[PDB]
Amino acid sequence: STGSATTTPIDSLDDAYITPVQIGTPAQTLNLDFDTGSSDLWVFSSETTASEVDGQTIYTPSKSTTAKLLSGATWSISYGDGSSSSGDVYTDTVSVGGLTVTGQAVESAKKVSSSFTEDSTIDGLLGLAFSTLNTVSPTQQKTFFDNAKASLDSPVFTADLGYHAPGTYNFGFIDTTAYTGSITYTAVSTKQGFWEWTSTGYAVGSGTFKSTSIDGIADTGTTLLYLPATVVSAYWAQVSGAKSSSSVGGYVFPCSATLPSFTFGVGSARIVIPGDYIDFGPISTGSSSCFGGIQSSAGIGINIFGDVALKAAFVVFNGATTPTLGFASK
View 1: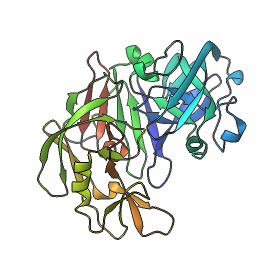
View 2: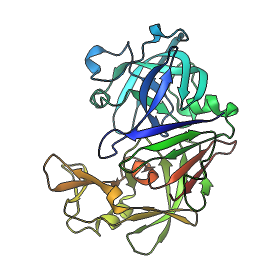
View 3: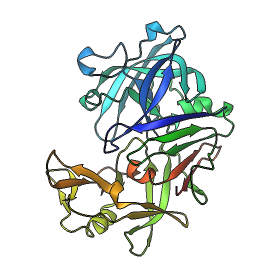
């Protein structure tokens, strides 16, 4: 089997992407944030604290003839930005782009952090990291991908995120028309439960490539590119007037600037992030200070290849017995 679904930015900055997902019988379509950095499929629901729901579409398990309470199961998750959610668990039929999993754990939120409440466009998250990170207790649950894997034509999914435009998540096949050149594959460590890999270096604009190993995770659920302070300083030093602002919470730059590109290495291959992808716009409405799309990972504890990086590539998440990650230009 295969599936193919379009993913759409939630706003004009590509702050996140939402993908429609069918849950239950009859189908209830919710728009979920597909998240290769976590492993829980959770939704706003009829059980979510009412004051914490603000425009989201909710899953109502009592209206699904295939929903079943997973008795005794609870979940609770915290993301690296401080966002969180928790609740109980149902199993139900879940379909993405024509690919159907029966008995999928659908984690119903009883509580969500304000950061989720305020995102009216995001009805929940669909985790695509390794199932070892799943937070359901006392019986850990499998991701949608893990459940689908054996039925898929090939045990892979691909992320093809757009810049200020829709893109595609495919399951079970590689669309050879969706990228240019060849796909370069690189090793993955699953020890921490993430799609963790090692970039071979970087370049700033038209500068020379610096060969250096940068361990990080491929995280579709993180907006920006978080890299070591040395790398990030080297980038922003090429933008007149750019500076790290403690009050704002990262690097800002004059909105009048033209940003240089940023290149990262994948083996001997190179992925180029155009400068425009690194512009996250005014820090507040009407400001001439703009927020940068490349930020320091210092104090996160891990480097994160988020959407800024991933949307410059066609990315293969290869879930074979020994997982790997593939990147192609597009």
